[PDB]
Length: 257
Length: 257
Ligand SMILES: Nc1ncnc2c1ncn2[C@@H]1O[C@H](COP(=O)(O)OP(=O)(O)OP(=O)(O)O)[C@@H](O)[C@H]1O
Ligand SMILES: Nc1ncnc2c1ncn2[C@@H]1O[C@H](COP(=O)(O)OP(=O)(O)OP(=O)(O)O)[C@@H](O)[C@H]1O
Ligand SMILES: [Mg+2]
Ligand SMILES: [Mg+2]
Image (cartoon, rainbow over all chains, first blue to last red; front, side, top):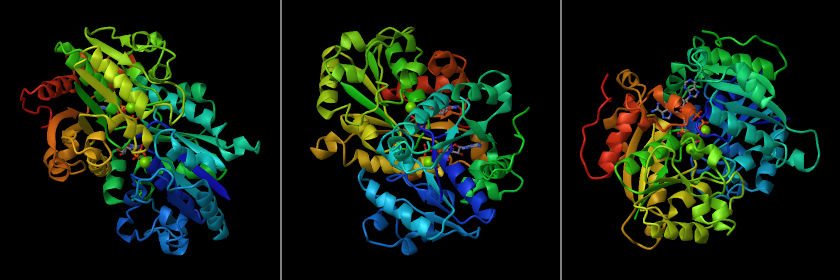
């Protein structure tokens, strides 16, 4: 029911990190969840969730009738009710079609997935447009830096004009701001925008703030989404985010020096 | 004569940082240089070079006959023989055409530019393909992490199959590896791939290693390409890179802790 795109425009801000962590948190809360790699050509989700060697069929194979969801969905290694739909290594802009994508989303809804997390590619070309097109909600992943922040602002424009909902005048895509790689030291020395600074500029509700954290690269190398590291500030920050996404309120930690 | 694309596939590895720095180093060595923003419509090069307020016309305006190069080219603020061709804020995948782009490149060659540095968008969709299509050389911008490194490998495949040169069997695009955000501490603790590790995997000649450096965000905020900061390891690393690009050999510093 809740299709959430993880987007940014700006490259390398942490979309996939966030997609893996958030999808895992949701599933840990009992919500049946699939996280989908929309980053066709340059797949990465399966590496981050550490299910690489179980990749048999992909998003494109399914669209193209070469495999069913049942064949393509990978059951997560660590967390119940979590599934992964990996991206094709093929490059082919049209490979993902609106019609195909739409059908996949209908089919997953039909498997009673509560949450469908869509890991977007960078940019605002067709790759990222596809990823957000059918979104109900959007997580704008933003580093507290001018460029990330500008690109995020632009992404908002696109959310409000080139999504299905914005083209058919339905309720607009719900917008969540997720600040990532927040370095409070750097912020007090005036090189990064404060949480507040960014909020003034973007003007959407903050869903999370993920501290800059050495545990994230470690999580990646292990193929273990950081949230599974219970001692990691970044992990806790993601658990908090998942709480906010589910209606609970939580104070924002790891934002002070 | 030397058209060099700065590419990566992987988002946020530092293509624009590198483009600005390298383009500036070349011009500083007396080589007439233009650096072009291919990242339409998430433009960023003009921010990094700090010429934002002088943006009048862009890459698309020129293609579309709405302006000439002379009207669109921005003369750099600090460095002689350096010019900037900013990207359009418009979003339109076709906005840049092969025919248009090709013509622009011919015209710049005609203004006797020795170096044409092309700042690529992330990904391997049409944005990045356009950026590398007419390349003579390619700077593969890579963070010493598994994903960056994988995507860089993939970029190489694309360089050797979907560039003009690879489609007409001309001399292949010359491949330069540029390791960025190299954190020697992290590397010795086994979280980042050593310079050597990456070299085994990518297998192209190293042109530079840019240390992780707080000066880079400072450079960006200032709009002063980091190479102009003479006290910055990152800047020195870029000056070294420019030396290597021009045939000189230099040992790789800031790689040890
Ligand atoms: N909280 C954090 N602390 C430290 N490093 C982080 C954090 N979040 C992300 N990173 C780093 O940022 C880089 C990009 O992460 P990730 O691949 O998730 O970003 P992305 O936006 O999905 O990238 P792309 O644009 O290629 O899709 C990685 O090097 C990751 O380690
Ligand atoms: N040597 C470095 N030290 C510290 N930070 C760096 C370094 N190089 C790049 N960065 C940081 O990495 C992030 C991305 O930089 P940049 O925008 O130049 O990369 P990019 O590949 O052009 O991104 P995109 O994929 O959006 O085009 C920025 O936060 C920048 O400050
Ligand atoms: Mg990603
Ligand atoms: Mg860039």
